[PDB]
Image: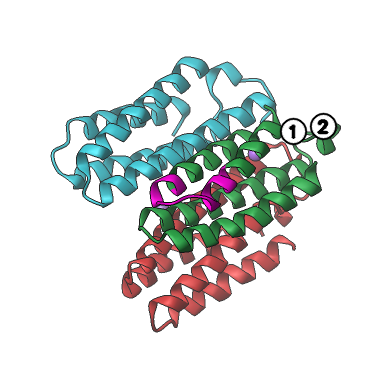
Chain colours: A red, B green, C cyan
């Protein structure tokens, strides 16, 4: 898939967490988010489509997705312990990175 | 360095997990698999030994290994919590991913 | 931060864990270490100043940092369970990896 489909998947699952009721929906949505971030790691953002795949910008893109993946791991650890409200609070932080990375690499 | 030795290690530790009696053997084999996958991250498969290290193929290679690493993390989290049967079942999700990465990139 | 600042962060937090008393300091220092390693993944060590970011040396550099990250996660899990002594023992292995990385890439 392209980078934009993965962006849309992240946003949709973030809203799903925003509306979630129990811990299972949070776990499933954050797992889908992890998968979408791993997939987006293989994509080229539009702003970097004219750049070397070996450029430092591509490296920084991928390592930023690594940082996001580790924050997602933290949120998933919170959700696996049944912490619904804290998983949602942590996901509210994920949003400020997902939308930001969206606004820059657009 | 060598893709084949690490793929071996993966298969052998999968067998060890399947034939394991307690959670400790599962944990140890999963740690060995994690080490082998991290090592294979640096390798170049023969199907791509004629491609550039920044090519999309190499990127997909390394990111598929990251995906395998997160699957191994899930299995290890299961094993640490004492759910041996669910950990083995999750390791049965690892055999298919390992085999696909094998056939496609070997 | 640069490469040197991140390595100094890693060292400082290593000692903090080493002389900590409760689990909270251990988890705080290990979280600092995780952030520092993720940031250093985007760095260019002095011995690789002019090599391409997609060079095999740089790929091995980033994968060594991935190994460090997974060890950091293991220590963080041991500390979150309350096993402070096991966490510090695991962080002793963290010191080995950090110092080897500094001795090879300085
Ligand atoms: Mn974990
Ligand atoms: Na890379």
Determine whether C92 is above or below B18 in the image. above
- Label 2 close to label 1 by CB (< 8 Å): yes
Residue with the mark numbered 1: B44
Q: Position of residue A83 (x, y in %)?
A: 32, 71
- Residue at the extreme left of the image, as rendered: C21
- Mark 1: few, some, or many residues within 10 Å (few <14, many ≥20)? many
User: Mark 2 or 1 closer to N-term?
Assistant: 1
Magenta stretch holds residue B23: yes
**Separation of residues labelled 2 and 1 (CA atoms):** 6 Å
Number of disc labels = 2
| Magenta-colored segment: predominant secondary structure | helix
Write down the quadrant of residue C49 in the picture.
top right
- Give the position of the N terminus of chain A as an image quadrant: bottom right
Residue bearing the label numbered 2: B49
Q: Chain of mark 2?
A: B
- The magenta span reads B13-26
């Amino acid at each position: 898939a392209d980078w934009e489909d993965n962006m849309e998947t992240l946003n949709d699952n973030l809203k799903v967490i925003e509306k979630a009721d129990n811990a299972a929906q949070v776990k499933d949505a954050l797992t889908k988010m992890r998968a979408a971030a791993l997939d987006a790691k293989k994509a080229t953002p539009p702003k970097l489509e004219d750049k070397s795949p070996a450029s430092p910008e591509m490296i920084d893109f991928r390592v930023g997705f690594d940082i996001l993946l580790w924050q997602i791991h933290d949120a998933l650890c919170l959700a696996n312990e049944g912490k619904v409200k804290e998983a949602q609070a942590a996901a509210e932080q994920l949003k400020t990175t997902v939308n930001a990375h969206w606004q820059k690499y657009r």
